[PDB]
Image (tube, grey):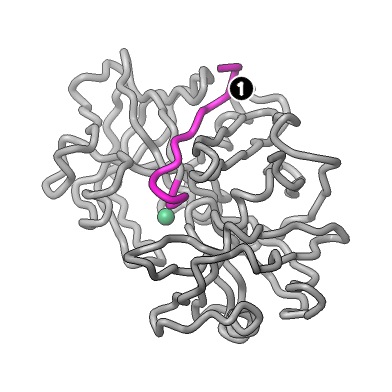
Amino acid sequence: AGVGTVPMTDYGNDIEYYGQVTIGTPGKKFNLDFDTGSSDLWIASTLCTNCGSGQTKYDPNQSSTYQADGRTWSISYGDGSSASGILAKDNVNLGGLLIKGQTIELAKREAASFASGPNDGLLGLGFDTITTVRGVKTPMDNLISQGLISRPIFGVYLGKAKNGGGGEYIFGGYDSTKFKGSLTTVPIDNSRGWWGITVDRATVGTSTVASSFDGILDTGTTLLILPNNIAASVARAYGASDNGDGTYTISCDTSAFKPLVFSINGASFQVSPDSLVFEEFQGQCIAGFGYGNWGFAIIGDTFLKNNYVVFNQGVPEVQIAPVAE
Ligand SMILES: [Ca+2]
């Protein structure tokens, strides 16, 4: 692959997307979840006492560039998962770009959901104001300061399992074969450490289901999670029924549904009919949109697998365009 290019693997029905990263000298390959909703780079390690037998574990002893650190870390994600351990320093190779002396977080403990998942840890792509340890420079901060990228951007393509899966992240560039038309620039609010944007409105057919609302672009969240009122308005448009757990039951037959269209900075971006269905289990379909008790939306994979995004940490801003398909 080209310089800074990282092919991704689509896990299951567009649940999450991970890529290979080489850590250490001579180095081991790790599958990490690329997450724009967090900013810590943590990996399963041989110090871990409740990690999955299937995860690849970083071993300090096998890296001649490992450097010990006296600090500890602990993280607790919104979904109830967590992990904790110690800090360390080592080299990280991202698509051919060798970051020297990146702060890495070695897990000593991790939640069972991580132990049974497909990845070895997470690569945080949010802003450095939300690293759990103060003073930690993120991989993007280091790519920029070490001169590994000449533009402070990363282009993101997330595939659809229905079309074969895959995905691709490009550090320092983007690929126009993955999108159609012109990119639309959208200003980012990074005040909470996330890629926050304002959606002007959301429509289903001729109905305005929502007025402007704020949301965060999160590759690390599977669904499109909306504030209660907005989610109910959307559900009413499709005849979806509330499962009482943050999810909805929708008709498995999407041939009759109109796309969920977001108006962002004057252009239209949509969640295609096929994406309105997340998963089918014993003939019952779970919708691609859910609700949470937050005042802002979590714009997850349901939305990102339909729209290419160029993330610019420098401005900050994003450039978006409909996926070429
Ligand atoms: Ca996640």
The percent coordinates of residue 210 (x first, y second) are 73, 79
Position of residue 80 in the picture relative to residue 302 (left or right): left
164 sits to left or right of 322: left
Q: Secondary structure at mark 1?
A: loop
Residue at figure coordinates x 36%, y 25% from the top left? 23
Start and end of the magenta stretch?
1-16
Residue displayed at 70% across by 28% down: 173
| 5 part of magenta stretch | yes
Q: Nearer the viewer, residue 318 or 232?
A: 232
Residue 38, relative to residue 119: is it above or below?
Answer: below
Q: Is residue 194 visible?
A: no
Image height check: is 235 above or below 167?
A: below
Q: Which residue sits at x=32%, y=18%?
A: 27
Q: Residue furthest top?
A: 26
Count the marks: how many? 1
Q: Observer-nearest residue: 307 or 221?
A: 307
Q: Which residue is mark 1?
A: 148
